[PDB]
Image: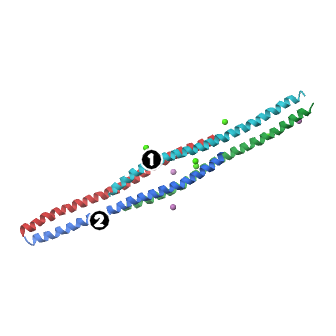
Chain colours: A cyan, B green, C blue, D red
Amino acid sequence: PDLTAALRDVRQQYESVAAKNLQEAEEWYKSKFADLSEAANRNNDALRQAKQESTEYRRQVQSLTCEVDAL
Amino acid sequence: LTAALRDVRQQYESVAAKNLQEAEEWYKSKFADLSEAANRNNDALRQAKQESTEYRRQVQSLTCEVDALK
Amino acid sequence: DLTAALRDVRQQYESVAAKNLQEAEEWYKSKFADLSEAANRNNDALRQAKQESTEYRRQVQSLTCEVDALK
Amino acid sequence: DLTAALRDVRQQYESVAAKNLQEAEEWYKSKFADLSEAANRNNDALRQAKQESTEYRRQVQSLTCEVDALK
Ligand SMILES: [Ca+2]
Ligand SMILES: [Ca+2]
Ligand SMILES: [Ca+2]
Ligand SMILES: [Ca+2]
Ligand SMILES: [Ca+2]
Ligand SMILES: [Ca+2]
Ligand SMILES: [Sm+3]
Ligand SMILES: [Sm+3]
Ligand SMILES: [Sm+3]
């Protein structure tokens, strides 16, 4: 088994394996970034609605107050 | 010739080692960044909640003041 | 939940990163072997061709010694 | 700034992943070359030695026919 034949043999193997690893890695990180993204928006919605309640109560406060005066 | 191989492997590990340390360091920092951003969002959520029930007890009291009043 | 998801992903990364670190640590070690064994056979073939080069070399040094002593 | 902190990290990753890919391709490409050089030089040393042995064998053949023709 020639070293030049052994060296080239490794080069085909590397080039192929390295090509497979990249593909898998890219898809993996895609999925993870996806999970986090979903969780982020989920957290975003919560903060969004929580703020709604607050400003909604604030509206009610100055709504009743707007009626306490004429009272 | 084996002096070429011995040279290569020692170069590989010296780099492979440096690569793992720099990578592990990199991920931990990114995880740190994200962790902080999340906590800040949690704090932000926890706060908007406290400021919601706060506003709620107020209207409960005001609507009571409006009722009893005439 | 971002915090809960971050922890999840963080664990998955540490999970695979260790596995992969081995599928490569072993692979790169099995390959440096093929080249290392090939280089040894190669270094041998030379040490064999060189010794042949000096094995036939001396043979000439004798046939000459016979041709002259007979002519 | 959730979606932002996530996007920043995704960009940093994609950026780092690129440089990691181009530094790897170089490193391996050169290390392979180096090994090819050594396997080539050695290879030549073999052919040079083989042609040398075969050269002498030619002599040993005809030089013997002279030991015969004479004797
Ligand atoms: Ca390419
Ligand atoms: Ca990540
Ligand atoms: Ca950094
Ligand atoms: Ca920072
Ligand atoms: Ca306040
Ligand atoms: Ca905005
Ligand atoms: Sm009052
Ligand atoms: Sm180790
Ligand atoms: Sm670097």
Residue A9 appears left or right of D50: right
Tell which subunit mark 2 falls on: C
Point 35% across, 61% down: residue: C39
- For label 1, the crowd category at 10 Å Cα-Cα, with few meaning under 14, some 14 to 19 and many 20 or more, is few
Viewer can see residue B4: no
Point 35% across, 56% down: residue: A6
Q: Position of residue D14 (x, y in %)?
A: 53, 44
- For label 2, the crowd category at 10 Å Cα-Cα, with few meaning under 14, some 14 to 19 and many 20 or more, is some
Q: In this view, does C22 lie above or below A33?
A: below
Residue under numbered circle 2? C47
Res C33 quadrant in image = bottom left
Label 1 residue SS: helix
Give the Cα separation between the discs numbered 2 and 1.
Answer: 39 Å
Please identify the quadrant where the N terminus of chain D is shown: top right
Residue B6 appears left or right of C1: left
Are labels 2 and 1 assigned to the same chain?
Answer: no
Please identify the quadrant where the C terminus of chain D is shown: bottom left
Of residue C52 and residue A59, the one placed in the foreground of this image is A59
Q: Position of residue A48 (x, y in %)?
A: 70, 37
Residue under numbered circle 1? A19
Tell which subunit mark 1 falls on: A
Of residue A8 and residue D20, the one placed in the foreground of this image is A8
Viewer can see residue B61: yes
Q: Where is residue D36 in the image (x, y as percent from the top left)?
A: 35, 54
Label 2 residue SS: helix
Res B54 quadrant in image = top right
Residue C66 appears left or right of B64: left
What's the amino acid at mark 1?
Ala
Of residue D69 and residue B68, the one placed in the foreground of this image is B68
Q: Residue C12 carries which label?
A: none
Point 15% across, 65% down: residue: D60
Q: Where is residue B19 in the image (x, y as percent from the top left)?
A: 51, 54
